[PDB]
Structures are given as C-alpha cells and as structure tokens.
Amino acid sequence: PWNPPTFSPALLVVTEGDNATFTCSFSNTSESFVLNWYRMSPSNQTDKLAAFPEDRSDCRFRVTQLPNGRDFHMSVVRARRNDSGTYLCGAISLAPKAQIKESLRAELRVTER
Amino acid sequence: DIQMTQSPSSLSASVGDSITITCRASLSINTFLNWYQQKPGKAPNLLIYAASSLHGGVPSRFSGSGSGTDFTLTIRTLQPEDFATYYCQQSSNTPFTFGPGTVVDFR
Amino acid sequence: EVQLLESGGVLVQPGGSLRLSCAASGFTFSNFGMTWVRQAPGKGLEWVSGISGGGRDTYFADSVKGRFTISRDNSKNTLYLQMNSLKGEDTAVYYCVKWGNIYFDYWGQGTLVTVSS
Image (cartoon, rainbow over all chains, first blue to last red; front, side):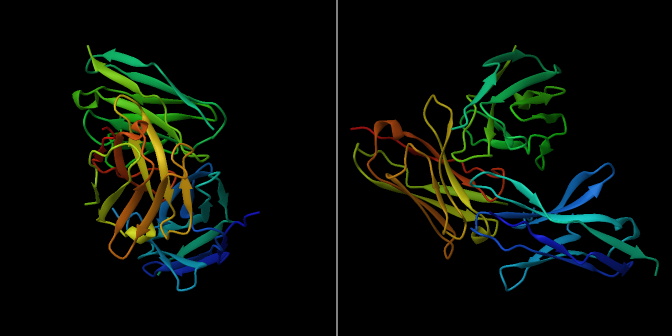
C-alpha cells in the first residue's frame, strides 16, 4: 500500500561540462523514509551516489529537495563522458518493515563538446 | 520480535590472525544487518551497514557478508586497535534488536 | 565534526522522573531522525525509542512504552527523552544516536542514569 518513487526524464542527454539534472518525485506516506541515488555498475551492481537526507561528510552528486514535498533534483556537477550509464532512485521504508522499493531506471548520455 | 544471536561468545587471538565471527537472526531480513565495535568505556562505532557496505573511515580489512538469517564479520589482518566487543543489529523490523555481542581478546 | 552531547543523567530514586537532553551539532538536525540506545551495566545494547526527525512519527520498545516519551525540538537542535515511572532495571548508560537510515551513524559518549535509593 506504498507507492514507489518515479524517476524522470527517461533519456537525459547533455554535453560534457554541463550539469545533468534528474528528478525523482517521491510522495511519502509517513516522514520516516530515506531516498537514495543509484548508478548500475557492470552486472547490475548498484552503487549509491548520493542520498537525501544528505550525509554531508563524491560531492559531484548532489540531491536537492524542492519546495513541494515530492520532487527532488539529483544533479551531476560538471558531467564527464564516463558518467554515461543507467541511474535510478530508491526509497527505503525504514521503521517499520525496512524495504527498498525502487523506481524505474533512466539513461544518461554525455556527448562530445 | 526478531531475536539475534552471535557465536562465538568470546575469542582469543593474536595480532595478524584472520577472524570470522557470525551472527544469526530468528527470521529473514536479507540485508538489514549492521556491525558495531564497542571499546571499553566508550560509545559503539559503526563498521558495516547493509551487511556488506563499509562505513566511512573503517579500515578495508573489516568486511561483512551474508543474507537472510546467517551473516559473518571478517577481520583479515587483526591489529592491536581491534580488540573490542562486536555487536550485530538488525534493522528490518521494529523493535530494533541487537546481538549479545562477541568479545575479541588478546592472547 | 558531528557531535552528540547527552545531559541529565543523575541518581534518581525508583518511581521518579527524569528528562534527558542531547545537544546535536555538526549536521542538519531537523533532516535526520534520532534514537536512544541504552546499555545496562553488564548487559548488551537495547534499542529504547526513535523519532522521525520532524517529530510526527514515534517508535518505542515494549519495555519503556507508556513510561518513556521521545521528543525533539529542531529549533535549538536538541533531542529529549522523558523518563517516567523509573525502575531499577532502567539503570543504564543512555546513548544519543543519529538515526535517519538503515544504520546508526554516530553515537554520543552517553549519560549515566542510576536508579537507586
């Protein structure tokens, strides 16, 4: 009875050096949640890039919460060519019954300048 | 309630040995295990989260594995600043329950 | 860096009441939930209570529910644990813990609460 977040745009194409920004919108039910940003390595191995609430202790991956309590920007700062890949966001339903329910994944294309 | 158990209860080893300690849960949690190190008279420190992810600043020799009910902590090359008590803690279901703890001693 | 400073641990007679305070500094306190974890003398770690971070959601253990109250005041970056109907069993070292994820990042050195006559 809890909906997963959605991850848009489907295909984000940017020129190298520019910042590429994703939007994961999560309509939380109760504020005991956490959103995570993932990048799929070879053989479907998920690496956590950043998260909200921001740990604040790579800094090129930042998560910003919009004035509405739904939309979030995951922005790569100064995107490189090797940042092209498959990305997705996931919500973990901690306290109680911790469950990672994932969004649909999105593709990032970084083109030559 | 999810009851957590650990084995061994106590451990004697010297510097350089490889140590593997286990943690068992009464029912499946599949990743939601944490490993903590407590030194005498001091607050516990986080070592492993999600049962295999290394917390920032923890030496790479510390490693965790396992899913479901059985998990393991591994210390590849034991060093003098590692002799302490280690607890495992499940985070799947409230209330959060800890393991009895495993004491690592100097021999 | 991140520091959690517990205060208020004093010898109290059984049946009394006491409130613990945690001074949070070094991180956005309002964005993270918090928990209290106690270690009884000679016993293991036991989870006491948890707060959502915005204060709307509260979680309690069976051993303290109805007797302990979890609260937070993000204006001054302080975490409170109101302890009522104290028992001798409740004598423990109470740790302020940074919640907000699967895992418990930082632990304060704790405050000692002794329940005796």
